[PDB]
Length: 102
Image: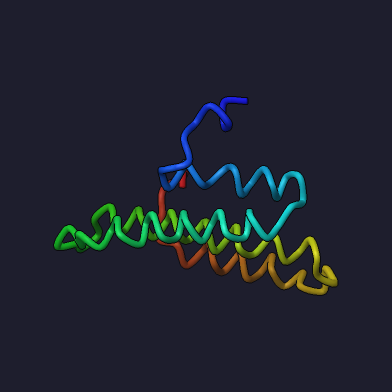
């Protein structure tokens, strides 16, 4: 509901819609939902913030999730043999030098 009630503009805006089509196990659009969310954050961070660790950093965390999202849609349509994903995730997380909420 509220997702519907959210616009499709934001990084977030596209986001859950993908999640949802993925929660609906619907892909192409959701696939492209990212692609916009991609495009969103595309233009976004590219202000570059003179970034050092700067929210373009967080913006990575954002896309990082998208990737991380881009992953599951393959799990979940894969042989589950992908189970390495866990490690990969484990990696993809642990190499995150990070706080929690992320």
